[PDB]
Image 1 (cartoon, rainbow over the protein chains, first blue to last red):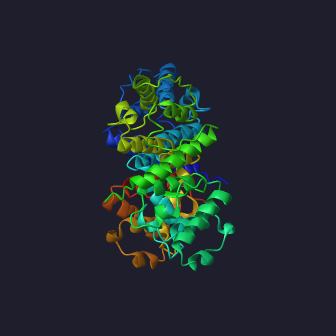
Image 2 (cartoon, chains in turn green, yellow):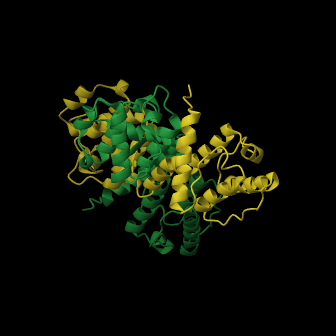
Image 3 (cartoon, chains in turn yellow, cyan):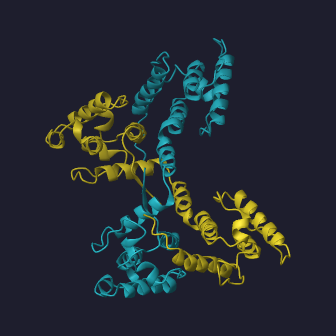
Amino acid sequence: DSYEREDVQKKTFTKWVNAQFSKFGKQHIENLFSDLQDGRRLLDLLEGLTGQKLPKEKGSTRVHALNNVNKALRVLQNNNVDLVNIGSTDIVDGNHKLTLGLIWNIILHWQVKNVMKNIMAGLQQTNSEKILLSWVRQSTRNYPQVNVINFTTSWSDGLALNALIHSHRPDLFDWNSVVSQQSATQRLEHAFNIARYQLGIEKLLDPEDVDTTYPDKKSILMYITSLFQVLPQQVSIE
Amino acid sequence: DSYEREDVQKKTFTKWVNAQFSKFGKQHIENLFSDLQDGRRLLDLLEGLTGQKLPKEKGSTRVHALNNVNKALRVLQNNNVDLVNIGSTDIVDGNHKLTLGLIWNIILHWQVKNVMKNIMAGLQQTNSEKILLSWVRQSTRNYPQVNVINFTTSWSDGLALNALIHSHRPDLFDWNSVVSQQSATQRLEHAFNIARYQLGIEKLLDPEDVDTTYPDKKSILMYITSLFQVLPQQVSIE
């Protein structure tokens, strides 16, 4: 259930630690189960990682080894690295499972959790309108009569609005019977009622605010935001 | 270029304001261009919105009208609603453009910007592994020989790794010539080199850490995170 290869983590985690020592022009380590024991190297990896200067104690002594690791554990704790169950004794007395654990937790912190930090940074280059438009388009990708590219004229014919509710709630009505209703005005009241009565959505709009040469962008946007607030919300980002 | 229908915003923004008075069991307004003039109603909408008690001044007087609007502008400013160019004189002297603007800015704050707040709340039910897996799968959707469902055994044959680089950089090599290379071990070194030499990616992995009955999840995860860090990052959320 794990396929936790301790022999493989020994190598790749050493390659990872060495690739960072490389980035900071620092000596490489060769054995992960004993080269992290005195605490000096953990402090150096933490220097390139953090930016701080981490004075290291002398020691040939266990005592210094332990000071050196406690300081690295405090630096790590300030950086919010998971450390549950990893003490300095464990690193100084060479517990290979917890030494691999510590290195995994530093890798998760500074590399694996960047996936999520880059996504959040991606949200930030983005506004709500664009997230909403992507949600409408993904929701309506299997409805060929619909092609949404704006919050104005893509909605006059009444299809996009019905397709969007339909894509989330196929249970509420039949796609083709909206498609053969030639009246746009009638596709619209249909969707507004399904949205008011099946979904609880207040009718901000009248068919003439949508079915018109110059529909109002803000009112449609606002209305479609109401649908988004109560339907599933899978969107694309970055 | 706008298709800014002031006649439509007058109605839908009144429907929006009334729908909130409804949610807080408050009186409806009927004319948006004069019913917001003394400041009392803006304070009531702000009560349901904010949770606060917004004492309102008496006044039949412009003076009180203005106090009433200044207090609502301060409440709004504390809530980070855009107010550039909207003063209380504008609301009290009935400037329909700025009254519509104020109401649009409150709607954007408390409704339209929930799209982006719900996405960020969605990231929070999610970890990096799952965002990465979705990115691999979306990146490799047009590569039929590839089907990624884990960070272990879906990568042993060497295809998924090559497909993922290929989907972002079709320029670097030829898909079919990786597909006809029967040696998995050889598809892997191929990808690691393309990643090391065309992409700058450090070879954390050896073909035997991947091409093996029990590949190590963490090492692959870590390695694939390196690719994600330098390739385009479109993912699916919520």
